[PDB]
Length: 138
Length: 138
Image 1 (cartoon, rainbow over the protein chains, first blue to last red):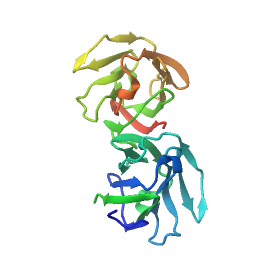
Image 2 (cartoon, chains in turn yellow, purple):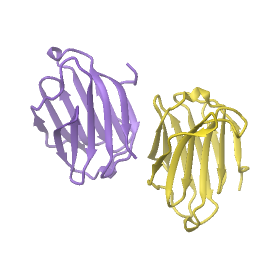
Image 3 (cartoon, chains in turn green, blue):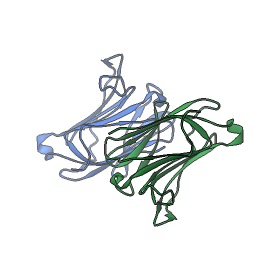
Image 4 (cartoon, rainbow over the protein chains, first blue to last red):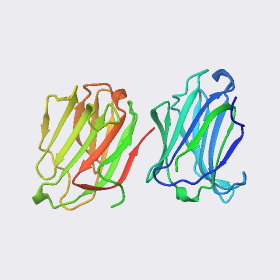
């Protein structure tokens, strides 16, 4: 649909920032489409990742950071508020100590800061979704 | 210290969830500082409270719910594992039938569910403490 995917936007984040995404999986959950949101330290896609958020729709969510090119300690959640076949609204809020991920208005995942959010210069949203909205507060 | 107080975080809870808090009273126990933790049904602070936990340090703990704006049956405990002048670690675990409150690793209070924990959308931690950690499992 509307926005290009992979979607890449320059961004600056601090406590009180919110990243809001509206989109739809490109396949039924039976086919395990993915969604990924990465907060990068530079505009280059190979740059380090302060917060990596990867949904396997209907299955699991994994979160991590990529530091000096290496994946760090993976965290996994089986919480799956996303609904098969439906548009979703995803909000990622920068709190003092963590990111909070809201899905369709419900707190669903958190991830403690491993690197200050001020290190972020770019956000990438990609994999098996269409995207109609991407917004960062300033 | 670290986190803002009053502290408000969106939250979702179910059986197996744990809310962990680390903090310190702002006054000696002789001055009866308070600590309060409220599990709310909405983000608004005037919303109903599924679980209200109020410590008068050195004195007593009261627990209650607030339903349709009205306080219900208050429960009181004189158990006081909190130590004068010291940092505390408070864990609130959602069990099938009740909340279990651990203080510094010891089971200290329980409160039977009056409303399903799935009704919770927000947690507020406030009154006479400083806060260095707040975490919800997902």
